[PDB]
Image: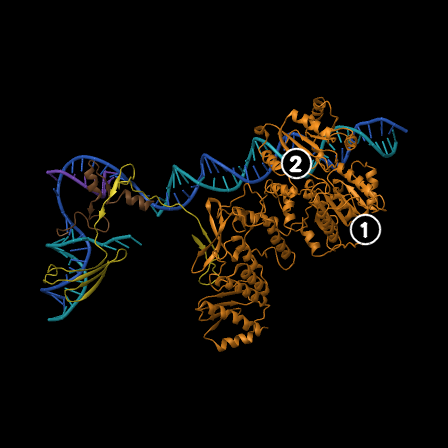
Chain colours: A yellow, B orange, C brown, D purple, E blue, F cyan
Amino acid sequence: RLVIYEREAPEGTVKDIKEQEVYMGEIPLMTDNGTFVINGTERVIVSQLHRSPGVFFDSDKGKTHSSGKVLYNARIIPYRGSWLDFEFDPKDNLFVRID
Amino acid sequence: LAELHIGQPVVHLEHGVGRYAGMTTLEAGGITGEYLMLTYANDAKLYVPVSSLHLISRYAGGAEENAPLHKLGGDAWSRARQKAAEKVRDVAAELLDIYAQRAAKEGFAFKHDREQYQLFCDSFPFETTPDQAQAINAVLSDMCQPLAMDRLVCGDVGFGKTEVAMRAAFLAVDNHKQVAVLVPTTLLAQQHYDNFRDRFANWPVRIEMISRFRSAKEQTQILAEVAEGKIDILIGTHKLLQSDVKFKDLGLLIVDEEHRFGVRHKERIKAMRANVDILTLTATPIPRTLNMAMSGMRDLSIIATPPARRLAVKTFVREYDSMVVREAILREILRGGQVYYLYNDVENIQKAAERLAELVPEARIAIGHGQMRERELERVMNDFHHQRFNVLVCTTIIETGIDIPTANTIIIERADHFGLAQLHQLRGRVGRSHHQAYAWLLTPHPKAMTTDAQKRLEAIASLEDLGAGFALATHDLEIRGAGELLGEEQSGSMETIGFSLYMELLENAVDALKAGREPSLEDLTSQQTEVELRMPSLLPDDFIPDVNTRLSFYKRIASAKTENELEEIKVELIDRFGLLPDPARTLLDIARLRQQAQKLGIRKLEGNEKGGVIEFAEKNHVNPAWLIGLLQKQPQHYRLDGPTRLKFIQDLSERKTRIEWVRQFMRELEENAI
Amino acid sequence: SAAVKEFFGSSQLSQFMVQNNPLSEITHKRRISALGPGGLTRERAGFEV
RNA sequence: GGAGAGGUA
DNA sequence: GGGTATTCGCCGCGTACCTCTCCTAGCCCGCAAGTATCCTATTCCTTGCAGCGGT
DNA sequence: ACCGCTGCAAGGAATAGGATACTTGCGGGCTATATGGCGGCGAATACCC
C-alpha cells in the first residue's frame, strides 16, 4: 500500500494512496511429513543448536597471560547486530571489544 | 440514477477510467480518513480522499459493454490528455471565433404578441398534449430572451413536433426574421411544405422551398427572393449549405432531425449568422450530441403523453419468412392500411419488387429508391401518399421521416446493416393513429445475421413501451459511443475524455483569449484555497451506511459557500439522522473555515499540534498593523514566514483547543479586517 | 527468490534426507546440529563443546 | 574442475 | 638506546574411499508477439457540369 | 447559335474488411556487510631505565 504525501502540506499529510496485490517470492512448502522438495530430491532442514542471544560472563581459568590470572570477560550477543565484549586486562583494566 | 453505480465506469483525470469499487476509511498517520476504491487493470486499487472528490466524474463515453481500464502508470491517459489539449488549443479556429464573438458580440430579442398568437392558437385544429405545451413554453420564452437561442425538441414521433416549430415560426414572422428551416431530405421537405401551406393558409406569410424539386431556375428565383428577404419561411435540404443562401436578415434557424446532418454541416449553417436563434429538432440525437444534450451546454426537452391513440408497435424479430410476409401483408390490407417493404439495394430493388409482386398477388406494389429520376420518385410518393398502392418495395429512403398515418405494417427483409436509432425511426413509420401498427423485421439466419444486429434486435424487441425514445437513446449512447467533441466521427469512442473536460479546456481557452493569460496559463489544477488542521473528519460508515448519501453530503460540503448552507445541512442531518458526530461537526466547521478564507483572502493554511503557517493573498483584508502588534506582543507564539506567510507556535494539544484557536482566530481577523 | 532458494538449496543445514528406513527418516528430521551459520565449524572446535 | 553436505574404515 | 615484554600476524592443525546437490547478479537490446487505427471496398443524399433538343 | 432542361459523373454521410505501423513482454546475451580455536614463533613495536 503506497501513499502520496502532499509535500507542501506539513508534517503529517496525504494527497493520495494506492495499493495492489503484488506477487513476490517463491517459498517452498512442507509436505505432510516434513520433507521439503527442492528439485525432486526431498531435503530436510535440521535444527541448529546455537548459543542464545544475551549476556555471558566467561573467564580463562588460569589459562592465558602466563600469570595464573583469570580474565573475566563478558559478551552482549544480540540476535542481530554487533557483538559487545568487555574484558579484564591482566593489569586490572576494562576493555571494550566490538566484534 | 446519474452517479455512483457500483462497477460503473468512472473517470479520474490523472490516471484514466476505472470502475467504482466502494468507499472505506484508512489510517494513514493518525488520520483514519475516508477514501474511495477505484479498480484499474491488473486490479490496481486507488483510494481517493473525500476532499479530492472533484477529480472523479461519470464516464461520458458510455461504452458500458467495454471501457478502457487504464492500468496504473500506463500513461495512455496522459497521452490522450495531451492530445486533447492539443485539440483544445485556443488557436482552434473552429469555435474560438464563436467564443471571440461571444466575448465581443450579442444577439436578438424576440418580442411576444399576446393577442395575434391566440389567433394562430385557434388555427391549431387539435388539443396540445401537456408534455408538448410546456415544450412550446420553453421554446417561445427562450425566443423572447436576447441571447442566441439554442434548443432541442427531441420528442417522440408524430407528437406534433411540427406544431412547436410552426408556433416558433409564427413568433419569428411576427418579427419577420426570415425563418430558415432545414431537414436532410427533399421528401419530408415537400411534406413539411404542404404542412406549412395548409396550416398558414391565412396570414401574409411567404413560405417557399429551395430544393431539387425546384429547378435550376425556379430555385434560383426562390434564392433571389431570399436575398431580397421577401420569403418569410424557407424550407430546404443541404442546398442551404452551398454558401449561396444569404438572408438579408436571418434570425431563426430550425434544424430538424440533426442525426443525419453531420456537425460540419451544423456549423456550416451556424457560421453564417451569428445572432441567429438556432432551433434543433429530432426524435433521436447522435450519442455525441446526446451527451452534449444531457450535459446542458444547450437545451433539452423530451415529449411524452401521446396525442390521441399512439401505441406500442409490435416488434417482430423474425427470420426471413415468406409466410410471415403473407400474413403481415394480408392482415395489414384487411386492416385497410399500407405496407412498407425495406430492401436497401438499388441494384436488386427492381428484381425484389418483380418477385414480390407475384409473390403477393393481392398487393399493389411500386419501387422506391434514391437512384432514379426525382420526378419519377415524386410520382411514386404521389401514389403512396394518396393510397394508390399498398406494399412499397423500397430502400431505406423511407427512413426520411415520411408521415403517412395510414401505413401500419413495415417489413424489413434484411435487418443486418442498420443502426438502432434508424430501426426506431423505421418503427416510427407505422402507427401515428388509432389503428394498430406491426413492425416485421425479417432476418437472415442468426449465425449469418451479424455481429451487432443481434444486440440491436434484442434492444429493439425488449424496448417497446411509452417513453422509449430516450431509453433507446441511452442505449444508442454506449452501443456506438460519443465521438470527438468538436471534430468529425461522432460514432466511436474517439478518446472520450468527457464533456466536463470541455468546460475546463474552454475556460482555459477563455484565459488564453483574455490576452494577458496564455494557453500556457492552463489552470488544470485549481484547489484555489486549502486548509488543514489534522483531525480525522469523516462521515462515519456506521453513522452513514449509504455511500451514495455520504458522497452526496460530501458534495454538499464542497458546494457549501455560506454558513446558512452549513446550518441547513446540519439541521437536515439531525432531522433525518439524529446524532451529531465529532468528525462530522468538525468538517462542517472546516468548510466554514474555507468559507471564511474565501471571504477573507487566505490562499493556504497549515495547522498541527504546535501551530502552523498562514499564506495570505494580495487582494486581502489582513490587518498589517494589528498583525505586527500581534507579533510584538507574542513573539513567543509567532514568527514571520516570508512576507506572505506566518508561522504560529501554539500549544495545540487538545483538538477542541485547536478548534477554538482557529475559530476565534479568524474572528479576530474578521474584526479588524482591512 | 535468490535468498530463499539459496537457503533451501545450498546451505550447510538444509541437507539431503537419507531415506532408506522409516527410522532414518525420523531420526533425520529430529537431528540437532551445531554447525552452519551462527555456530562453530567442524574441524575447529575443542572437547568441551 | 571446484565448493557444500552426509557416511564407512 | 636496550633488555624485556606485549602484541600480533602467520604458520600448522589424519589418510583412503563412497553417496548426493550445486556452481554470478543484473542489465540491455533487440526481437518476436499482440494491437488500434487507417486506406480500401460498398452504394443514400445534394452538386455540378456537360449533353442536348430545339429552335 | 443560344438557352433552358436531363442525365451522368463528383463529393459528403453511414457500414465491412484488410493493413500496418504502434506498443510491448521477454530472454538471451552481454559487464562487473564480520563476530565459537589454540600453541608457537619470530618480527615488529612499548617502555623505562
Amino acid identity at mark 2: Leu
Query: Dot 2 falls on which chain?
Result: B
Query: Dot 1 falls on which chain?
Result: B
Tell me the number on the disc at residue B26: none
Q: Give residue B167's position: percent from left, percent from top.
A: 78, 48
Nearest the camera: B92 or B426?
Answer: B426
**Distance between the alpha carbons at the discs numbered 1 and 2:** 38 Å
Q: Residue at x 55, y 76 (%)?
A: B625
Q: B413 left or right of B192?
A: left
Q: Secondary structure at mark 2?
A: helix
Q: B132 left or right of B119?
A: left
Tell me the number on the disc at residue B423: 2
Nearest the camera: B320 or B524?
Answer: B320
Q: Quadrant of residue B559?
A: bottom right
Q: Give residue B536's position: percent from left, percent from top.
A: 46, 61
Tell me the number on the disc at residue B118: 1
Nearest the camera: A47 or B336?
Answer: B336
